[PDB]
Image 1 (spheres, rainbow, N blue to C red):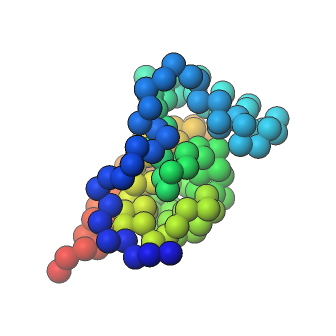
Image 2 (cartoon, one colour):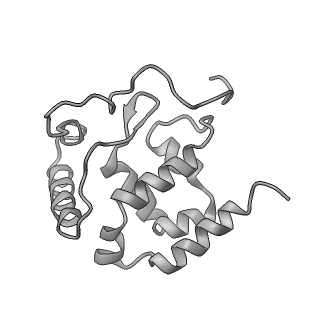
Amino acid sequence: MGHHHHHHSHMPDHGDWTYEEQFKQLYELDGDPKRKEFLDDLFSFMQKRGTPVNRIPIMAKQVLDLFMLYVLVTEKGGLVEVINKKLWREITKGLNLPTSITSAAFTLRTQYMKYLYPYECEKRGLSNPNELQAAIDSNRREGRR
């Protein structure tokens, strides 16, 4: 498995390639009706409020499965809840990601917040942007004395 020595960068992941392809891999993940519906409805929704998908973040050379990420986080109670539980270890493992990665919990927490958030608050009302900041700051204080 290997311990997290030093992240910074590696050989180009599949998300640093500038090509005019609509990220079809997300749809080709499952091939299920719910899969394409959520993804497309999401992209339109986030675009309307001025925050669409430019390029998708990569983890361990695989795509950050937006659909799967949203599923695991929402069933735990939403972004802020997951932050308050610090239980991101479950979120990574749910995407077949190695919890050994240095800032995995923080990286997912960032990318999710950017792309996957207005949907949980609008459709469900799970987390508010206000409680969110308090959650994050509480996570920040966990580092030094």
